Length: 305
RNA sequence: UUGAUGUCACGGAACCUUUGUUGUCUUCGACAUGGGUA
RNA sequence: UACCCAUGUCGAAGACAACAAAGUAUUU
Image (cartoon, rainbow, N blue to C red):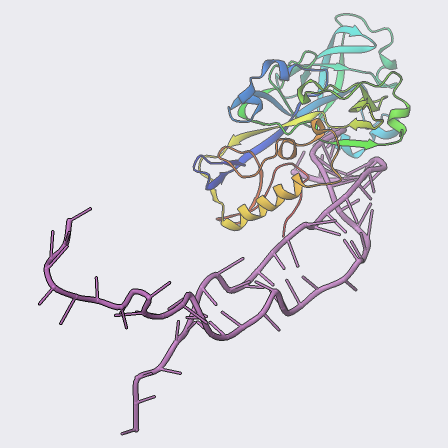
């Protein structure tokens, strides 16, 4: 939700999507303006809810784990090979929905047509395809995925790189870093992740670093959130109780002895010493038919009595 | 800024009454933080 | 729009509440 200009109502967004900000696969911090980052100018993003995945042998007669629930909802088509790189193969696809086509890169399974050993330019194959939730957004359409993006307008909710694990002693991620750990940056906008927790699948990027008095930090947030489809006709009134609870939430955020000692790793509410609701704020809200009941600044937050 | 044959104003204690007092173990364990994957 | 958690660290309270001036016969 978004707090209205009068400061007395909160309007409802219909949707959210994740925006990668601290990974090296994009340039959002270099191309978005300050008031777009601050969440006080609306922006227009490309959004994809579902992403396609292929198999080049029928899942129903595929060995092992693909006579499986995810593949129960099959869809069929034909694919044309057009490029190969790093063992990945590039296909244009036509599904059985008349004319309905898209390009995608595929990293073959062992049973994908002899793992595509010996396939050649211009060839084509019968295929099966599924779609799975992706719910991500970008300002510019990434290369290697040029199709299926929907243009939407909304606001960016930028909290900062505040999901951090820290210790006085070296854990599993730090032990396996393979390098000299960086120093803690001074500016929260320059942080970029430098390896992964699951380095085979390359899920879950992290930023590992060390400070001058011997603490080790692992920041494990790389996405930031995009709010879109603002409903004009759906205000909810903020009662006085909701403001008191929010002020108490802010007080407990800013008076924490157990807080991470480096403020670049704190959320905007704590890092910036926020003290009130203000017009135009972006927030998560709980409501009844007419009134706001609970307000929090981040996705997993605190609940006040 | 006096008025004149008449001024005890050195003719009148800012005096009298009121408790800085009432209540409070130098004690003590679970809590911080916000995403990630499809 | 469903699923899943992850990390180990750290002192708190340092006066508060009340009162903040009020009374002080002249007569059946």
